[PDB]
């Protein structure tokens, strides 16, 4: 019940989100490596 | 008056050692003494100006005397490429035996004068040591004149009235005409009468300068305006500087460009140059009214510039009042203008080298630029420091009722927010691109770099005729309006100097120009974020609005309201001095590593290895300190052993600065109590008791002395590395 | 070239002038 | 003037200069700074509740 | 390049030193 | 001496006197506040100027302001 | 030292032999009946006054300021009253008419020997 | 001089240098080694890496420079990731502004920035997609800016 | 704290198990440089995988775990 309220705090959301955008960049740089165009 | 601070009784009552340090550092603070009013202030700064000028001319007579007496000046005149310019001699009793073999150049053991002085004295036309002695006496006399005036205008009935000092109106009628206009005109009277004939072989010393006219016909049929005769026969190509071979006889020819042989500007160009600047300044001297009454009242010149658009407050009505009554505003404009002038000097001493056989010794040119850039940054930081002194101890927002200045203090929040924005943007977009290029180069791949061509500088070099880029615009295109418009006048003598890659004029440009020039603009915008911060928040911030009550360099406000370390307007100085040394750092590392690629020849060594940071720490600091740090070995030493010593010495200055900058007072204030306990309690030394009580340095002094060791350590380290680096790869 | 003059002036200004000038300035604190 | 009114300040040295705030106390006992006003945001001393006079006290509607 | 001009030099800056102490003991 | 001046924001809540470790500040009955109190600083010759008052001065902005003035023996706070 | 500097002599009385802490450092014996204490500077002495008073009842205490000419002064207490407690004998000095908001600008105090708050 | 990159000679010398220099590590392993397969995929990631720079401008260094004039012959270098990037941080800036002007009026705004209302947070996280014509329609409404906020003395 | 230390040491023994050349290092220790951590192949950083022998590359150990394991007798 209050566990999601812990998962709504500043650092936990910042790691579940920057982990996600970091995953967007790392998974988007294995699939499309050396992207200097566009 | 009673003890020490014969000027402040608030410090003579102090029993500690603070009376000494604050007695020193508030000595020239003439606005805060016991009873020194305005007339007693201007009548003291006016005398101390003369004492200062006499110190300057004592110094230049110092250079004239040592070059006259211990240097090798005329032997240098014999072969200005080969022989190194010697400075003053040495007397160490510490040079045991092996040092002296590393300094003998002839009979002398002298230092090598890496200050460009023989070049400028060689283009003046000094070709002897005798003229240097007569000049050195000629400036000892002048320093005696200036000390006579400063002693003379502090004699009581010759102390001038303050209404004379508030003839602000007419100093500009006399500085622009007499100081700037006449003297530069007088300097053409040197260059026409000395530098042109003693460059064209004719020894026109002090004898025949009235019997040998510099043109073979002159001034009786030349009030008629046949002035093309003075630019008739230039010195075209086949001339060596100093002899009479291959040279014409015209005086004021504006060829434009360089010598073919000495790679310096033509002295005809400088004679015509200072002549035109002379005429335009003498015209500018006729600007303001006096007792005559033909000119401009300054109140009518700042009052009239109130726009009816209404956006710019109630105009400049209030500015002329706060320049007469102020001084730190006037000193802020003085250091601003002198500082931009110094940076202009530095950006033109290498680019258009004025002095014959400069850009041939690659150390003096590397020291003059760095010299005028660090002096440039020092004088900008002076302009903003006295800006904050103006906004605290000199600013009246009731005479400046909603003035342009009060408008500035109104939107200072937008000013500091946008300086912080552009500084943040450049700091994530130089450091982002250098760490990008450095990661990417580090990962076995120099190709995946971000290199942006700095096309705006390449286009501006295309506007000045550098055809090596392929834009074909105003001067690079040989058929345009400006290209035809000066086709005979100064273009073909000048585009040869532009399109050449030997000279240091309009350099070839890679993306290192891009990333570095963004780093420089980062330095300017950070340093103005700080200076404009604690110059506009100099007076009152929302932390403490009492700041105007505490003066300029008050320490703090204690731990109250969160903590208040360095809130003063003196902090903006104190921090933007680090940013000054840093920014002028990157300017002179960039310049010096650009020209260690030109002078070596491998420009590709720069342009391939300067787009990332291990290009700098590898290809410039690690490699060019090799002839430095071999200044003395366990196998011996050489002539660089001074600089390699000084280098190390300067690191010991620099890090001692950190002892004052990092670690603050209350450590030491309770450690001096242990030292004074131990001195009081011991036998054989409790007799020798102090008079001034031992007290650790106050936290304005401490940050100041840590700043002073940061500057002296920084500047001595880099003056060691410029001179030992270029003097190690050459000479 | 009076080569002997640094052997006089460099000591008498290098060391003994910041001895007697320490005396003049430091007694001049108390004058 | 009255309790609970949302009040902008016109004294340039407050932390809440040109920021509206709620009036807690109005004292009618000759105090030079009678109107105790607290705020949403908080100055450096951790203290929103301060007090003011009547000239520095502009209500809204 | 000679010696007598060096003596004349330190005479003139010795006099200039007397103006330095002369200006110095008035401000 | 460090001139301590106590302005008319001083609502007399005595954290200044209880915060000052030197008894330079006392409380004076002054019929201008709700509490009827306003601090005074008579013995500023003993004033260190540590600004521990201005930490615990819960006024709007600092009824009590400590201007750093002269530096005597006691105001420098040296032990010997 | 005692030949040229002011030694501050804190005198006070107690009821039991407790143990306080010196401002020099380390514990002291705390004579139960009545005891003096020569100290160096005033912050040590009133720091001992806070050292005792925030612990327990130690009142009727004050430093006699021994200055080296010989005589004494009466610090702390001054008026048999505790300083944050209000006595109607202390005459106020050190106030102005308003806040900082009416202090004059230092360009009006410039070239005069006034202060930026005097009005 | 900015040569087209597919025919710059020293550029192709960097191709030979990185393929062959990376192939010097390939002279250690057998034909079925997973390391050797990784250097097969790595050589693929060098030839593709250099053939996919065919329309850049590698100058005298053989290193692909860029252009920031918006020449429209080099818009894929800078201005298209410029518009793309300003869209992404106009998203982030608009989401942050909209979320703060939500939680400025809640019960406990101090608690709302520690513990994000993931209901209303992930409301605005997605809802800030059309921020050019949402900021342009709030800017015409007199709501994007403010007036008479805090300031120091003068 | 001991939970983090056992997660850490279990990390060292598993990176010695799965990722390291320790069985190859145990053949000739003076030739094969010790390595455990085998860097994931993204842009460039596969160049950090040092060919340390043992038929497998990766960034070289300097913590000396393998010398603790040969002393331990882990075969
Ligand atoms: C949280 C960020 C994130 C996101 C958005 C993705 C997204 C994706 N991953 Mg992925 N991945 C992530 C983190 C993430 N991954 C992490 C942290 C790991 C390490 C355990 C992996 C390991 C991983 C593998 C091993 C594979 C993917 C694959 C995929 C793709 C499946 C469709 C998709 C693009 C698959 C794919 O398409 O690759 C071929 C695939 O095989 N991912
Ligand atoms: C802040 C300055 C800055 C800038 C402008 C860039 C810009 C770039 N870097 Mg980079 N980099 C930087 C700093 C910077 N870097 C720093 C400081 C480091 C060290 C950590 C690196 C390390 C680094 C590596 C290791 C690599 C790059 C690469 C790149 C390029 C492609 C980025 C990418 O992954 O695209 C792919 C990402 C996307 C397509 C995501 C965008 C999709 C959006 C979010 C979806 C939504 C659209 C609506 C790009 C030119 C890559 C490259 O090939 O170099 C040219 C690359 O491999 N950079
Ligand atoms: C801006 C004004 C200016 C300045 C700074 C100088 C400076 C100088 N002149 Mg000079 N000069 C000037 C105007 C000036 N001149 C004018 C207007 C004339 C024409 C009358 C001359 C005519 C002149 C002669 C004839 C000689 C100098 C020489 C010199 C040099 C040594 C002077 C000395 O010993 O005392 C010195 C650099 C001497 C020199 O350079 O030695 C070769 C020298 O012989 N000057
Ligand atoms: C024609 C008359 C005349 C002249 C020549 C001067 C000259 C001077 N006045 Mg002055 N003054 C005058 C009339 C005049 N005044 C009148 C009528 C009044 C009353 C209204 C005053 C009131 C007055 C005051 C109140 C003060 C002066 C001061 C000064 C001195 C300025 C400091 C200095 O040397 O800068 C020299 C500066 C330059 C030579 C130029 C600097 C900038 C240029 C652009 C750069 C240099 C050019 C070139 C690039 C570099 C050459 C270097 C070389 C190595 C290549 C200077 C000697 C001040 C001073 O110091 O007291 C003595 C001062 O405080 N004056
Ligand atoms: C302020 C500087 C200055 C001074 C003091 C003189 C002074 C003199 N010039 Mg002169 N001159 C100057 C600048 C100066 N000139 C400049 C800038 C030019 C170039 C336009 C000339 C060009 C010039 C010519 C062409 C002649 C003189 C001549 C003379 C002499 C007689 C008139 C006199 C000594 C005449 C002479 O006899 O030369 C010595 C003469 O024929 N001058
Ligand atoms: C011609 C230019 C000029 C003039 C007239 C002034 C004049 C003044 N400045 Mg100043 N200033 C200038 C340029 C100038 N400044 C520049 C260029 C800067 C930036 C670097 C500053 C930065 C500055 C600050 C930060 C402050 C002043 C202040 C003052 C005022 C008092 C100065 C004083 O009492 O110092 C007394 C004299 C000294 C302290 C001697 C200087 C010694 C310095 C600190 C270190 C040098 C030691 C040296 C490096 C050691 C040698 C060893 C070797 C190995 C190198 C006075 C009106 C002060 C002021 O008005 O506040 C009340 C003040 O706080 N100035
Ligand atoms: C290496 C030394 C260093 C660096 C990088 C900086 C950097 C900066 N200083 Mg600075 N400064 C320094 C030394 C340094 N200073 C020193 C010695 C002094 C004298 C005390 C000052 C005094 C000073 C003043 C007085 C001011 C600054 C300001 C600034 C900022 C300028 C704006 C800008 O460029 O933002 C761009 C941002 C950066 C360059 C930050 C670096 C980027 C980081 C590394 C990436 C983010 C973290 C990264 C993801 C790693 C994560 C860590 C991991 C644990 C998770 C910038 C952060 C000013 C400011 O606030 O400007 C707004 C300002 O007013 N500085
Ligand atoms: C709510 C999001 C948000 C928004 C819209 C802005 C907007 C702005 N900031 Mg900024 N800022 C933010 C958060 C934000 N900031 C945070 C969290 C910090 C602390 C790191 C800063 C620190 C900061 C400084 C130091 C400066 C600005 C400045 C500026 C202005 C110039 C644009 C710029 O360079 O940004 C700057 C951007 C950064 C420094 C980094 C980006 C900030 C975060 C990481 C991105 C936003 C994500 C945010 C956490 C999302 C929260 C909501 C979500 C959970 C629902 C602009 C108005 C500058 C200014 O005054 O110019 C006028 C300036 O100098 N900001
Ligand atoms: C704080 C203060 C201050 C400040 C200081 C300073 C430092 C300033 C700044 C300023 C500066 C530092 C300056 C600069 C200026 C700018 C400029 C001046 C720029 C512009 C440019 C231009 C102009 C150029 C252009 C051109 C060209 C390129 C060629 C053609 C033509 C022309 C010329 C147009 C003052 C005193 C004021 C006031 C008080 C306070
Ligand atoms: C084109 C181009 C370019 C550019 C340039 C320019 C364009 C510049 C200018 C600049 C500008 C033109 C600027 C403007 C600005 C101004 C202002 C005024 C601003 C505004 C801002 C704002 C308003 C913000 C806000 C926001 C938004 C909007 C969204 C969300 C977030 C935020 C909230 C932050 C270059 C060269 C690069 C390249 C080529 C092309
Ligand atoms: S450290 Fe000393 S100076 Fe810096 S803030 Fe705290 S008290 Fe004021
Ligand atoms: S001023 Fe602040 S501290 Fe001093 S009494 Fe009034 S409230 Fe208590
Ligand atoms: S100044 Fe320092 S000592 Fe005097 S009262 Fe304020 S805080 Fe206590």
Image: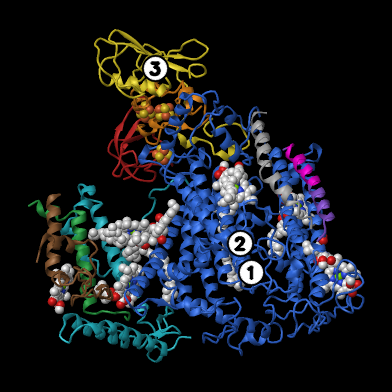
- Give the colour chain D carries in the figure: red
Q: Residue at x 20, y 63 (%)?
A: A17
Q: Secondary structure at mark 2?
A: helix
Q: Residue at x 66, y 61 (%)?
A: B111
Q: Is mark 2 within 8 Å of ligand 4?
A: no
Q: Is residue F44 magenta?
A: no
Residue B386 in view here: no
Residue B526: give x, y in percent of width and height.
Answer: 46, 58
Alpha-carbon span between mark 1 and mark 3: 70 Å
Residue at the extreme top of the image, as rendered: G33
Q: Residues within 10 Å of mark 3 (few under 14, many from 20)?
A: many
- Give the colour chain E carries in the figure: purple
Q: Report whether B402 appears left or right of D50.
A: right
Q: Which chain is yellow?
A: G
Q: Residues within 10 Å of mark 2 (few under 14, many from 20)?
A: many
Label 2 near label 1: C-beta < 8 Å? yes
Q: Which chain is orange?
A: F
Query: Which image quadrant is residue D10 in?
Result: top left
The part of the chain drawn in magenta is E14-26
- Same chain, marks 1 and 3? no
Q: Which chain is cyan?
A: H
Q: Secondary structure at mark 1?
A: helix
Instruction: Judge by depth and name the residue closer to the eye, D8 or B29.
Output: B29
Quarter of the image for the C terminus of chain B: give it: bottom right
Question: Residue B139, which numbered label?
Answer: none
Q: Report whether B587 appears left or right of E25.
A: left
Ligand 2 quadrant?
A: bottom left
Q: Which residue is mark 1?
A: B349
Question: Residue G76, which numbered label?
Answer: 3
Q: Is residue E23 magenta?
A: yes
Q: Which residue is mark 2?
A: B372
């Amino acid at each position: 019940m209050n566990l999601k309220k812990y998962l709504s705090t500043a650092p936990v959301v910042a790691t579940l989100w920057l982990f996600l955008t970091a995953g967007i960049l790392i998974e988007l740089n294995r699939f499309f490596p050396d992207s200097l165009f566009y | 008056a009673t003890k020490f601070p014969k000027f402040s009784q608030a410090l003579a009552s102090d029993p500690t050692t603070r009376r000494i340090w604050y007695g020193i550092a508030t000595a020239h603070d003439f606005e805060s003494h016991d009873g020194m009013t305005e007339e007693n202030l201007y009548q003291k700064i006016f005398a101390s100006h003369f004492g200062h000028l006499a110190i300057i001319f004592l110094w230049t007579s110092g250079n004239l005397f040592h070059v006259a007496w211990q240097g090798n000046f005329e032997q240098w005149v014999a072969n200005p490429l080969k022989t190194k310019p010697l400075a003053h001699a040495i007397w160490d009793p510490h040079f045991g035996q092996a040092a002296l073999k590393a300094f003998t150049r002839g009979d002398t053991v002298a230092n090598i004068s890496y200050s460009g002085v023989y070049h400028w004295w060689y283009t003046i036309g000094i070709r002897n040591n005798v003229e240097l002695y007569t000049g050195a006496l000629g400036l000892l006399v002048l320093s005696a004149v200036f000390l006579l005036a400063g002693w003379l205008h502090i004699q009581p009935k010759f102390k001038p009235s303050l209404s004379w000092f508030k003839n602000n109106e007419s100093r500009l009628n006399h500085h622009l005409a007499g100081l700037f206009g006449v003297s530069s005109l007088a300097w053409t009277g040197h260059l026409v009468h000395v530098a042109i004939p003693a460059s064209r072989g004719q020894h026109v010393g002090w004898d025949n300068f009235i019997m040998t006219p510099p043109h073979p016909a002159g001034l009786q049929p030349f009030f008629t305006g046949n002035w093309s005769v003075y630019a008739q026969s230039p010195d075209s190509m086949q001339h060596v500087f100093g002899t009479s071979q291959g040279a014409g006889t015209a005086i004021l020819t504006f060829l434009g460009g360089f010598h073919p042989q000495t790679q310096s500007l033509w002295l005809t160009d400088m004679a015509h140059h200072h002549l035109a600047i002379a005429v335009i300044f003498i015209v500018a001297g006729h600007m303001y009214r006096t007792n005559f009454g033909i000119g401009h009242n300054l109140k009518t010149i700042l009052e009239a510039h109130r726009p009816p658009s209404g956006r710019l407050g109630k105009g400049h009505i209030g500015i002329y009042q706060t320049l007469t009554n102020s001084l730190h505003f006037q000193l802020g404009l003085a250091l601003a203008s002198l500082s931009v002038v110094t940076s202009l000097v530095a950006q033109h001493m290498y680019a258009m080298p004025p002095y014959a056989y400069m850009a041939f010794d690659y150390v003096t040119q590397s020291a003059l630029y760095t010299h005028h850039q660090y002096i440039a940054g020092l004088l900008i930081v002076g302009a903003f420091a006295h800006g904050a002194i103006f906004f605290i101890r000199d600013y009246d927002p009731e005479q400046n009722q909603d003035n342009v200045l009060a408008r500035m203090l109104a939107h200072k929040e937008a000013v500091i927010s946008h300086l912080s924005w552009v500084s943040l943007f450049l700091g994530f977009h130089t450091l982002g691109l250098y760490v990008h290029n450095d990661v990417v180069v580090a990962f076995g791949n120099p190709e995946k770099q971000i290199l942006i061509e700095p096309i705006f500088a390449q286009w501006i070099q295309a506007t000045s005729g550098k055809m090596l880029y392929g834009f074909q615009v105003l001067l690079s295109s040989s058929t345009s309006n400006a290209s035809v418009a000066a086709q005979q006048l100064w273009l073909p003598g000048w585009l040869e100097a532009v399109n050449n890659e030997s000279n240091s004029l309009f350099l070839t440009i890679g993306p290192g120009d891009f990333l570095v020039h963004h780093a420089i603009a980062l330095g300017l915008h950070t340093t103005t974020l700080i200076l404009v911060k604690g110059a506009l928040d100099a007076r009152g911030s929302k932390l403490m609005p009492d700041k105007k009550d505490f003066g300029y360099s008050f320490p703090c406000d204690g731990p109250g309201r969160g903590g208040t370390c360095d809130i003063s307007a003196w902090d903006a100085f104190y921090l933007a001095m680090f940013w000054m040394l840093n920014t002028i750092g990157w300017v002179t590392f960039y310049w010096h590593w650009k020209h260690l690629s030109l002078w070596q020849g491998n420009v590709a060594q720069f342009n391939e290895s300067s787009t990332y940071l291990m290009g700098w720490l590898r290809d410039y600091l690690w490699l060019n300190s090799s002839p430095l740090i071999n200044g003395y070995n366990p196998y011996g030493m050489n002539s660089l052993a001074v600089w390699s010593w000084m280098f190390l010495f300067a690191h010991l200055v620099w890090a001692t600065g950190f002892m004052f900058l990092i670690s603050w007072r209350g450590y030491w204030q309770e450690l001096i109590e242990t030292l004074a306990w131990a001195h009081e309690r011991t036998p054989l030394a409790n007799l020798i008791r102090w008079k001034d009580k031992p007290v650790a340095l106050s936290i304005v002094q401490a940050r100041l002395v840590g700043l002073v060791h940061f500057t002296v350590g920084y500047i001595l380290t880099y003056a060691a590395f410029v001179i030992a680096s270029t003097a190690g790869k050459f000479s | 070239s009076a080569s002997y003059l640094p052997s006089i002036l460099v000591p008498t200004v290098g060391l003994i002038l910041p001895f007697a000038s320490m005396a003049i300035l430091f007694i001049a604190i108390e004058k | 003037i009255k309790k609970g009114s949302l009040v902008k300040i016109l004294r340039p040295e407050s932390f809440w200069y040109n920021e509206v705030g709620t009036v807690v106390n109005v004292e009618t006992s000759k105090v030079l700074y009678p109107v105790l006003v607290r705020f949403d945001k908080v100055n450096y001393s951790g203290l929103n509740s301060t007090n003011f006079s009547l000239d520095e006290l502009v209500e809204i509607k | 390049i000679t010696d007598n001009q060096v003596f004349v030099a330190l005479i003139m800056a010795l006099v200039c030193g007397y103006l330095a102490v002369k200006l110095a003991k008035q401000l | 001496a460090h001139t301590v001046k106590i302005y008319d924001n001083c609502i007399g809540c005595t954290q200044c006197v209880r915060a000052c470790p030197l008894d330079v500040l006392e409380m004076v009955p002054w019929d201008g506040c709700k509490a009827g109190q306003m601090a005074s600083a008579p013995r500023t010759e003993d004033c260190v100027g540590c600004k521990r008052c201005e930490t615990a001065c819960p006024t709007d902005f600092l009824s009590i302001r400590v201007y750093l003035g002269g530096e005597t023996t006691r105001s420098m706070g040296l032990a010997y | 030292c005692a030949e040229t500097e002011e030694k501050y002599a804190m005198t006070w009385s107690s009821d039991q032999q407790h143990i306080f802490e010196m401002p020099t450092g380390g514990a002291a014996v705390m004579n139960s009946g009545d005891n003096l204490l020569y100290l160096a500077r005033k912050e040590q002495a009133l720091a001992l006054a806070t050292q005792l008073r925030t612990q327990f009842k130690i009142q009727d205490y004050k430093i006699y300021r021994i200055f080296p000419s010989g005589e004494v002064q009466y610090l702390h207490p001054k008026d048999g009253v505790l300083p944050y407690q209000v006595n109607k004998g202390r005459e106020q000095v050190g106030r102005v008419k308003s806040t900082i908001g009416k202090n004059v600008n230092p360009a009006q105090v410039k070239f005069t020997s006034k202060a930026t708050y005097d009005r | 001089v900015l040569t087209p990159c597919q025919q710059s000679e020293a550029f192709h010398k960097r191709e030979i240098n990185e393929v062959r220099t990376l192939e010097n590590r390939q002279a250690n392993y057998e034909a079925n080694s997973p390391s050797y397969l990784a250097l097969q995929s790595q050589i693929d990631q060098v030839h593709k890496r250099f053939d996919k720079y065919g329309t850049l401008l590698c100058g005298q260094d053989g290193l692909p420079h860029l252009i920031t004039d918006g020449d429209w012959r080099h818009a894929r270098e800078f201005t298209i990731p410029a518009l793309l990037f300003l869209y992404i941080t106009g998203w982030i800036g608009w989401v942050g502004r909209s979320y703060l002007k939500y939680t400025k009026e809640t019960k406990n705004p101090t608690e709302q920035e520690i513990i994000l209302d993931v209901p209303m947070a992930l409301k605005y996280m997605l809802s800030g997609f059309l921020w050019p014509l949402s900021a342009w329609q709030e800017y015409r409404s007199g709501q994007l800016l403010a007036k008479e906020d805090e300031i120091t003395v003068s | 704290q001991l939970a983090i230390i056992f997660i850490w040491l279990s990390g060292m023994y598993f990176h010695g198990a799965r990722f390291s050349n320790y069985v190859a290092w145990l053949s000739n220790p003076t030739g094969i440089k010790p390595s455990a951590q085998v860097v994931w192949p993204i842009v460039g950083q596969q160049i950090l995988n040092a060919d340390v022998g043992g038929g497998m590359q990766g960034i070289q150990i300097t913590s000396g775990l393998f010398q603790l394991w040969r002393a331990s007798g882990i075969v």
